Length: 287
Image (cartoon, rainbow, N blue to C red; front, side, top):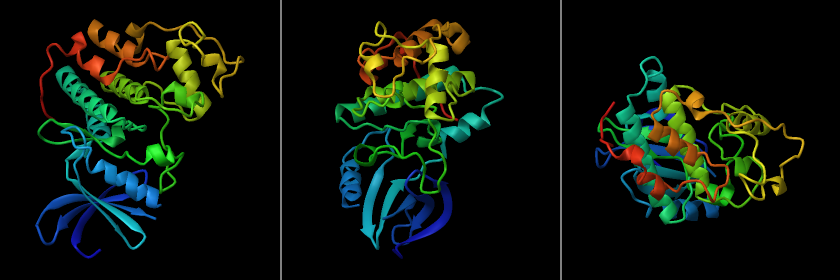
């Protein structure tokens, strides 16, 4: 490319490496992602150039050159995974949990209003600044290519944040998949512990059943007709959420419960969740 100077590698996303880089012409400091290459990828990333929102990482340009796709992004400060790790002793304060959950729902509501799914929400894919904003990153190829099992580095793509409709092998995905993922992140921010740390598809599903109870045709009409559903699934009782995410207050447990509804058609929308009593006292603090 020979137009930007790489200052440092800052990450490996699902599809490619990411560099802090400095535009040699504009002095501009960017995040530069490089994906090794097909034409469908390029056309899909181009639609992202229009998906602008304060809670989506700003895509500044897309360059198809030399069997490579470079994405130029605005430069933020750290991923949420690092901030959660850094905070494991103290715990992220609630108003900041509340602020971040508010902003992510705002980002999802925008995406979902334009029928764009993230499909791979997780702390690794959320970027914060010093200003106390949080942003959706690493999405837009999922509609076309789905979610790979592994990264370009052959790292395992975590299942901890996958909706059960996906794990049970439904091949048509609603916006509800993102709400599940965000519910998982919410609980993790509170408890400083992954809600459903599965290491396999069936291990992920059984962790979900152990906490929320095994779904049946009552809670989830059609579920036992899912492609990968087995009548031989063990039948666990639903657990008290007071056990699951202490010491989250009643409004939090109630929002979370609606975010982890088994039936994607009963699961709260981004837009509904923004109206939830849990956000009545919402503010905007910083790390």
